[PDB]
Amino acid sequence: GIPKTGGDKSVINLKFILAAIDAHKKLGWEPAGSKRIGFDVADDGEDANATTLMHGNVIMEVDEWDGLEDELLKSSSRVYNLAKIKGASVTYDSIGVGAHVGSKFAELNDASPDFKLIYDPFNAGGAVDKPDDVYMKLPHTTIKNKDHFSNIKAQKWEEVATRFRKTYEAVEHGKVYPFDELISINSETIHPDKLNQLCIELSSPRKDLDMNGRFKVESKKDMREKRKIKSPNIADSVIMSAILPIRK
Ligand SMILES: [Mg+2]
Image 1 (tube, rainbow, N blue to C red):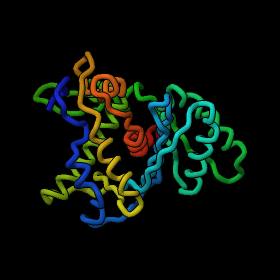
Image 2: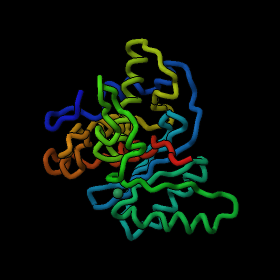
Image 3: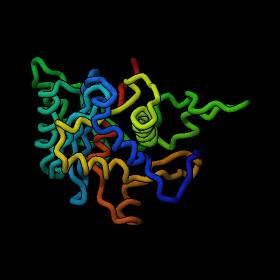
Image 4: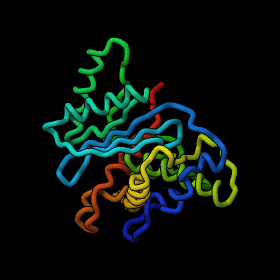
């Protein structure tokens, strides 16, 4: 329903995530579309760097590695080379340590004669895409995107959750959607440990409220302090890998 605070409701219901595992095999489509990498950048020892590779609407690869700011170059190079091998764009956490990532990418693009990496910064607290669009129509007013979402992070998290929910509807209830509106997790290219961790992490952050009454994702800080839960870096990389480019 409406955005609320407290409770224990996941932004992405675990049963949606389970239903999405090999959902493209169950429903009958193969990965087709743009290739995108989400790159979450570690900020403390409590964090790890995470990458998620999606092809179209299918999560294809997940990876995790340690590294702080003083090896950022190496990390950046890693993500660059992955992007060159997979032929993918990159959306990366651009706050904190990530504020120093763009430079690195630029350098590599400047040295590359053939490959130009398309990379976009993602500021979780930034403004929502299409703020004046209608999120929900009412008898005489409309809830706008700017009325429902606290920030762009909430917007992207709910967009991915909507993908998972439609996928659950299609798998468990036989409901019909255009396949591009769904999402799938490719088990054959993801280690079972990583698949389990992905399922746990994506369903870890809870629904919350900002002080304007807009939907907000439970903060990492609140997860760590109020609930003593590790940072779901892989889930953040997944959310960033699902982001579709805007302005053209
Ligand atoms: Mg970060």
